Amino acid sequence: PFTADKGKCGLPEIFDPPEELERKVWELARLVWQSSSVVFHTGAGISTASGIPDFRGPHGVWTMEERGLAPKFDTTFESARPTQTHMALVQLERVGLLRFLVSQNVDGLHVRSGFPRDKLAELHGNMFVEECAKCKTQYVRDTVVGTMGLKATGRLCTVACRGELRDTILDWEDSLPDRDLALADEASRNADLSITLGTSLQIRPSGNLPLATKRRGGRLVIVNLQPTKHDRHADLRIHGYVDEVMTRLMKHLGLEIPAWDGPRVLERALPPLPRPPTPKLE
Ligand SMILES: Nc1ncnc2c1ncn2[C@@H]1O[C@H](COP(=O)(O)OP(=O)(O)OC[C@H]2O[C@H](O)[C@H](O)[C@@H]2O)[C@@H](O)[C@H]1O
Ligand SMILES: Cn1cnc(C[C@H](N)C(=O)O)c1
Ligand SMILES: [Zn+2]
Image 1: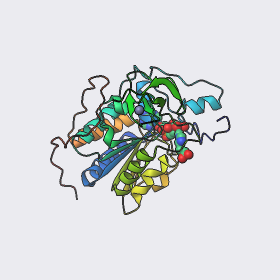
Image 2: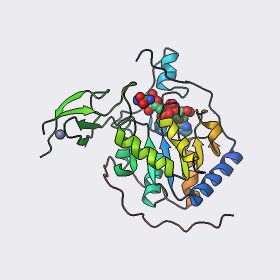
Image 3: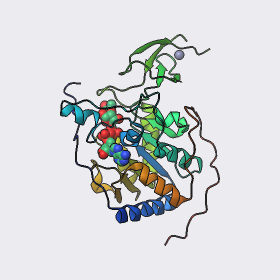
Image 4: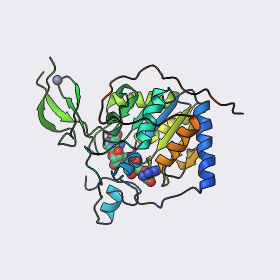
């Protein structure tokens, strides 16, 4: 807890110049077009533009702690809106260009964005989600579950059980949920493209899952302002705000970023919606 290694914090930000940034996002568009199975890996950097601080950025939770300062929230978890990046990920799954989505984020924004829970692994848990110890039935609440560390919330199961509801928020020593890690690992291994967005990739095994794509000739794209553990293994590193990257990419793919209708929970993905025909590439 007090001793827990919080990794490299507050490393300097990298900004690709405008010409290099556009070339790289056109290369990312080329990679998504060519790839059969695209897996996205998200961390705290995809929520910074909705007022939720990350952990290891210049004003990260751990970075600020290291300097004896406090992280700053510009939102509650309840009033936080999915970013352009969150909504881009919704659309990419809908049109069948996203196979699976692996997130380290506990902020609940993927679920609340309307992203289908059967194509999502929430490796570190979800602050709005509590789970019955007896029957493992999960509840997606409209308010944050008041506890962290897999503790009793004080509510009981209502399945046709009265089992003790517990939060899904892993503490440092807790291993990943077997179901989410198993599906995330399978998805990453089989992927021919793994794209990382606002994660420094410093937490095992979460941060390592993109590397699994590299086995069998898979391609790895890392989008991050700061350096990441696995920068040297990337076929492409894009240093820029994830919203600028994802909005340019969606424009290149000929996709609109959909409207958020407010907080909505989707258990199961649908068959793909129509998508634009693919460019002639080579
Ligand atoms: N708008 C942005 N655009 C691009 N990159 C961004 C942006 N905002 C921040 N970043 C980058 O986003 C990156 C976020 O890196 P980290 O802060 O380590 O978050 P994690 O999700 O990988 O942390 C994993 C676990 O560690 C914790 O203990 C928890 O348990 C987490 O679940 C930084 O490098 C920023 O440069
Ligand atoms: C944030 N976090 C919590 N637990 C983890 C996984 C941890 N490295 C383990 O497997 O034991 C990450
Ligand atoms: Zn139950």
